[PDB]
Amino acid sequence: AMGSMERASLIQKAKLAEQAERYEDMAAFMKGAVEKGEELSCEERNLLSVAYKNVVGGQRAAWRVLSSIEQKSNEGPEVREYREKVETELQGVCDTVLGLLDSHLIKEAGDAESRVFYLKMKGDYYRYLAEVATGDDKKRIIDSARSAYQEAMDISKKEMPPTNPIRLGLALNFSVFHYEIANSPEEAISLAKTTFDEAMADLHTLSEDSYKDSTLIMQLLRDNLTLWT
Amino acid sequence: AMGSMERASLIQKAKLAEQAERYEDMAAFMKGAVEKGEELSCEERNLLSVAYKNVVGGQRAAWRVLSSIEQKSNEGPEVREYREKVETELQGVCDTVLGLLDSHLIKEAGDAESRVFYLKMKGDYYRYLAEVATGDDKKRIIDSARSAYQEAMDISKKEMPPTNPIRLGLALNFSVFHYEIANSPEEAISLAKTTFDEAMADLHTLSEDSYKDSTLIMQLLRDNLTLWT
Amino acid sequence: AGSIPGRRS
Amino acid sequence: AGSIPGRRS
Ligand SMILES: *Cc1ccc(S(=O)(=O)Nc2ccn(C)n2)cc1
Ligand SMILES: *Cc1ccc(S(=O)(=O)Nc2ccn(C)n2)cc1
Ligand SMILES: [Cl-]
Ligand SMILES: [Cl-]
Ligand SMILES: [Cl-]
Ligand SMILES: [Cl-]
């Protein structure tokens, strides 16, 4: 994609699109940057993730509105048809992200920071597919999410400190997976609690700026525990 | 557009898209409904207008962000290129709306309520074109906006009460045209003041619900006068 | 200066 | 339940 634009120009334009809140443009620019075939820096991985999280976030919010309307009507075909249209577009965005991870971001990611980041992304976009799945592959989709999150957890436990923001965001989202997708609220609560407590005990090692980064995500873990218990 | 979907289904789906905040979908559904060739009801005209106002509103906000960045840099080509891309997309949306009005919404609009509504729309989308115009046709674009607003004003003065919400919104936007586009702040202020005062004097004729509709738009006229004086 | 918001209906 | 917002960077 965007094969005639320079890699650095795509990156520069992705940053401009974020400033303009043009997330679909942002995602297309970062897709083009990925397809240049070079590995992504820390900042570039964040741009990729921010772009697609925004795009699919708007699609998920729309799908939920329409699914709610459709369920009320089942207590013409237009509501179902339009929910299907949005659902198909959402699935296409998830497939696009998963295809970028599989060709070839993950296999070239050797460092813990990049490999865990991409595997967390892989778990997230299978989780989004699972949110809308209802057929013969719901279980396989859930298992693909679980497997990606689990491999990322294993690496992050071995290779990153308990306060690392990627390690914390990964555990947060895997706990949401357990609660919302896998029907395992006790696993969700246990993971969030253990994650929060082990980060708390490591905060003494951090600078002021890293402390702010870690405690912000710890608060999200606490907010979920408050809702779940 | 959408030539295989029923008119009533397009309308129903436009309402669902508004609920899902899917304004690009909403606009495409209403474009399809217009192209069925039948006149639009009051509610259908509102759906058309809401859809495109949202789409072009997001494009205008993005263009302004990028134009500001571009002007700062002029105190590589990427900022200019990306502002041009957004600008071209915005112009295409305005041309699409203007094409719907010209083929054939306006010529079939006989009643004052529909004809003034469409002519106000025509002035608005030429005004949006004028906001980004810089070349040999800036003046002609401004005159096309002025002409559309003026014909709508003439009809609304003859055919609608001074509190009619369309008449008030038309005068509000024409006053913004004078202030922001035509470099005529005194005309803008005079129009907003006379509009507000003549509506005030007609409020006694209204029901509770119509009074709420009119005073809400009168407040917008007052807010502008507060900023302008 | 605000035009009519006109973004909800 | 909130996942990481992750929508600004
Ligand atoms: C999955 C994930 C992505 C980014 C980060 S971050 O770098 O720490 N940015 C961040 C932190 C908290 N929030 C809401 N965004 C962590 C995890
Ligand atoms: C141009 C215009 C369109 C719609 C209306 S309305 O029907 O009165 N809706 C409305 C009123 C105030 N606001 C902010 N929206 C008036 C004018
Ligand atoms: Cl549809
Ligand atoms: Cl590598
Ligand atoms: Cl561009
Ligand atoms: Cl007619």
Image: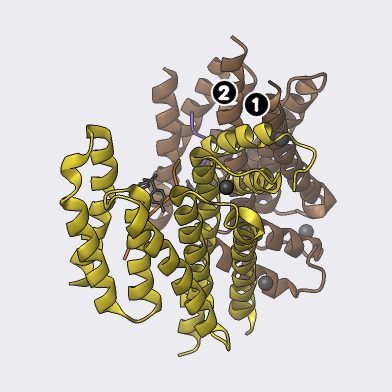
Chain colours: A yellow, B brown, C purple, D orange
Which residue is the site of mark 1?
A: B79
Q: Chain of mark 2?
A: B
A61 vs B177: above or below: below
- In the rendered structure, which amino acid carries the disc numbered 1? Val
What is the x, y in percent for residue B115? Answer: 71, 49
Q: Quadrant of residue A22?
A: top right
Q: In the drawing, does residue A229 fall left or right of residue B101? A: left
Distance of label 2 from label 1 (alpha carbons): 7 Å
Nearer-the-camera pick, B147 or A146? A146
Mark closest to the chain's N terminus, 2 or 1: 2
Q: Quadrant of ligand 3?
A: bottom right
Report if residue B56 is visible in the image. Answer: yes
Q: Quadrant of residue B60?
A: top right
- In the rendered structure, which amino acid carries the disc numbered 2? Ile
What is the x, y in percent for residue B148? Answer: 73, 35
What is the quadrant of the N terminus of chain B in the image? Answer: bottom right
Please give the name of the residue rendered at 46% of the width and 53% of the height, measured from the top-left corner. Answer: A117
Q: Quadrant of residue B217?
A: top left
B86 vs A68: above or below: above
Please give the name of the residue rendered at 75% of the width and 44% of the height, measured from the top-left corner. Answer: A2
Please give the name of the residue rendered at 47% of the width and 64% of the height, measured from the top-left corner. Answer: A124
Do the numbered discs 2 and 1 sit on residues whose CB atoms are within 8 Å? yes
**Disc 1, SS:** helix
Q: Chain of mark 1?
A: B
Which residue is the site of mark 2?
A: B69
